[PDB]
Amino acid sequence: DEPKVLIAEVVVEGATPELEQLVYQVISTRPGSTTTRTQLQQDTNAIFATGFFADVNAVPRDTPLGVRITFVVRPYPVLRAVQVAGNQVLTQEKVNEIFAPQIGRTLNLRELQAGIEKINTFYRDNGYILGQVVGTPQVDPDGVVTLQVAEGVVEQVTYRFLNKEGEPTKQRTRDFVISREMDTQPGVVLNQKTVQADLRRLFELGLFEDVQVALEPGQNPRRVNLILNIKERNT
Image (cartoon, rainbow, N blue to C red; front, top):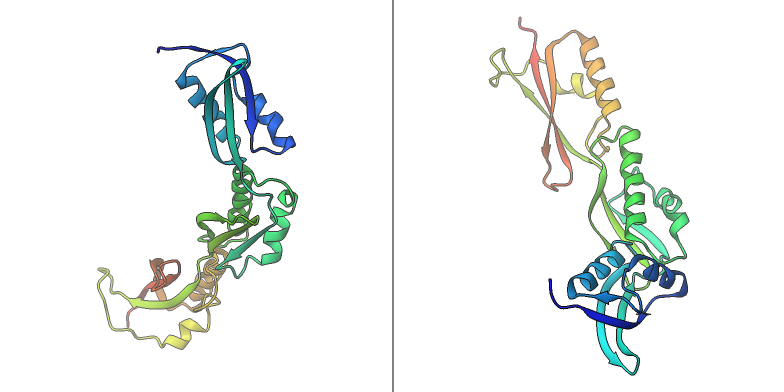
């Protein structure tokens, strides 16, 4: 863990005033302090961990005073808007409301992740069990952030009839009999409350020994094929 250098000045470049005090607060390197390469590296890690910066570099130069450490920092842009692709039950207006407190100051990726968590909580609490933000947020240099969601859209619903052993068997009941009990239909976003309700209506018909629900990925792999595995009461 050698060698050590004495520092004469520390400057922060590239930060707005609000953030520049933060940089000084989180680093340990001061004028008058002895540092190594490792510690300077840890200082850039600490600054990066604040969540405000796209890029952090520590640069040492020789000045008339002695050694300068310049921390060069490239903040994320001021946040101007957050827009979403692939949404249906999550409205752009709800997205605007979640992120309103952040608009007009430098974007912070920890705070963005807290908003992403608010979106996933909106899906989960409203019963859209599959719904969530997917991918990495796109941050454009003009301060507009784009997110993707996959809400759990039902591409198709497939009935599979099975005998007692669990092998395929000839269907007796007509498709309409089942379909007309179900609110879960192609094009809706899967909701665990509606699935439940649907299975209760299928039970109230008195026709099936078992109905089990299984999901397979759609053709669009962000969507689902809802499978009903159905064992009908014999003759």
